[PDB]
Length: 49
Length: 344
Length: 50
Image 1 (tube, rainbow over the protein chains, first blue to last red):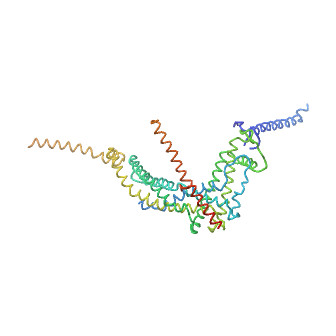
Image 2 (cartoon, rainbow over the protein chains, first blue to last red; image 1 turned 135 degrees about the horizontal axis):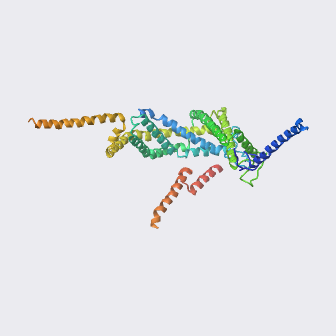
Image 3 (cartoon, rainbow over the protein chains, first blue to last red; image 1 turned 60 degrees about the horizontal axis):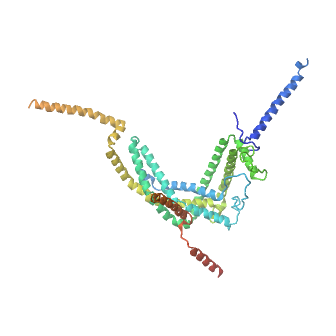
């Protein structure tokens, strides 16, 4: 899908600001996911040396 | 056989149906909720349907409400509605009888018949309508309901209101699937409901986007909550219509539904008397004569009788065989005249 | 003016046919003088008072 950005307020269908605030949410999700992965990866034995 | 079958009770049911559609328009436009806008609602609040059973019997508001409703329903073009509806119906039953008739092939001729019935109905339409308006004059002033009819109007009203209930529920389901997921329209309902109470307030500086919701998504949600509040009002007015207090007529201003249906039915039936004599009978006398004359005018002025024969396959084979037999007979007759000449 | 006569005339009839049906829907075309109203009200007030 691709969405349009017609209704940018909050509280309602899918707003243009709701949509934007989702976009940053997913990002903070993936950056979290890669952060904790990378924490595991720095704690692995392959990084000891 | 059809005219011995149609009669009067059918015009009874058809008119009575139409007049139901009419009762629902009146009952909503005088008593129930309306469309929805953003700014929070009026109380209203003397006009809440919920306290009708426990409201003062000498309420000026309800008195004027039912009186203007009934006056209005009567001073409607019930004559024209009768004349046209019975028109569409007689037309319909004629077009269906043609369908089963010997005239299923031969489209020219079928159309000639159908247009003939139409022109006779079009002819009688006005005098039927007038006469109906003059016959209804006395019930326009005082349409007094008898208890027996009031029982009838109650049983009818229960069926018509609950059906309208299911039609509100379905328009809803079509709103839901139109908008997307039912849960989204439940989200835009929650935004409309919250704005309808005191919980949230929106000022109207940007009429493009309010909440996270499009300008149309919000319109669709207002209509959604409307349908729902109308669905709630209907189910209640069904329950109060079944209620013990509505059993008697004496509280007529308490149960407008059964009242207005009784009025609809009585008008429907007296209209149905005049309409059965004048329009229908005129139709049964005039229609065969018109069928004959327009067919005779079509077939003889158009020379389409021969094509009328060509249109059916079987009879065309029948008529085709006879020609060769002809040509050979005429030949043998010329031969005979010769043989005569050459023998004496 | 004569050539505009046929079009202007129908258009007045249209406005009139509308007014007449509004008289028909509103009030059921029942006739009314101001005097007929004041008379009815005055006859009600005179029965009430007495």
